[PDB]
Length: 224
Length: 194
Ligand SMILES: Nc1ncnc2c1ncn2[C@@H]1O[C@H](COP(=O)(O)OP(=O)(O)OP(=O)(O)O)[C@@H](O)[C@H]1O
Image (tube, rainbow over all chains, first blue to last red; front, side, top):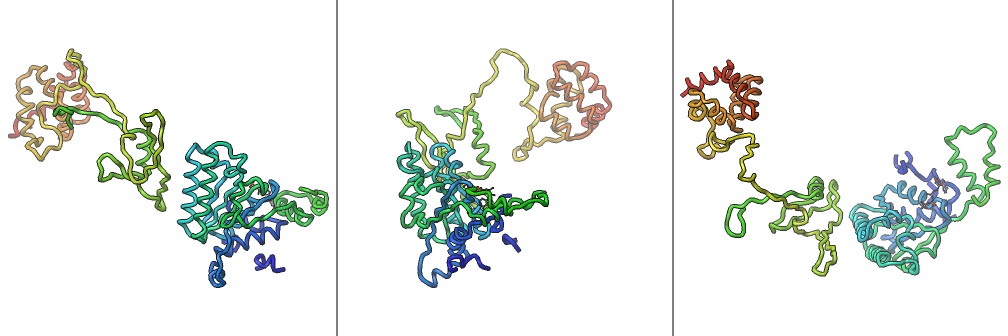
């Protein structure tokens, strides 16, 4: 009812830039939540000024790998049409000592400089694991830099941070407080209708034979 | 520039391969302090990351200091060593010259290349003989460039002239040149010119 009130209505404002809402299936509720948290603060920022609140920014998606977290983030970013800065966990962590912090600093600085922006920190568990797993001093410098950049952003507004991870506990607890990744979204395995939608999405360019029963495959595939 | 004692010593340098790759993407500019070079901003075309310059302290530890405002240029240099050939006469030089016919565009001073200077420099040797004297007067880099610019001699004549002036075996080539029609016209007009 009200929950999916944002989903109701060329395409994609008209590579990996072509992903859109039509390339996703079986996650109506989570997609509604993500869109309600991302589009409204950026596309229509005057609603919250009119009602007199500061919308939350940090969004933390998590679920089993393969559930489409990166797909959802990229689709939302491409549909919003806002300055989209993509940070990869391993890509930042592969840099030399002292560069993996400067990269984060410049990333946030650029995202703040430009127009309404979205920062997607894919695989945040790589750059901010639980303290017991943060072996070494560079693993602590990076976490502290992430925390400082997150804290210093709350004033700027018109910039939303999205993070994805496999498990809620895999992240440093200090990142899940007020003014940080406070709103949390959970992606679960799809149901029969979701699996049918995914199957239709993927098998739209194949030379399928006429004797294909995608409903049967949807019924058989459980836990996929 | 001059050495510590007050002389006219000469020094040779060469910028590193990263300064060479830094200037191409702008990213550097001169600063009012002679020893330090400025850094530009992240405009919409050129994107400058954070620049660190690494140095080792007296305790043998490398220290990285952020230098956005300005950093010394001593990290962008490598020093060569100059010198002169030993007094032993090897005579591998290509020219017994650099003292005579005026050099390139020094019109500010009285050094103005013109037909009168040729008539006074490279005419008495060409009016007497002494092929050795003519060869040592013809082996001047700037004289060769000037006569080329005169365009009186045809390309083959100038090729044989340069190979007569720069090659260790020049007797036959020098004789061919002095006997060549182009050289004869050149010397005739030079004599006629005053
Ligand atoms: N509705 C859907 N849900 C999930 N995946 C989908 C869906 N529709 C298509 N796919 C495809 O499934 C794969 C999902 O890969 P994806 O990178 O999104 O997974 P992920 O584990 O969430 O990501 P990552 O670990 O990179 O953050 C891609 O091939 C995507 O094209």
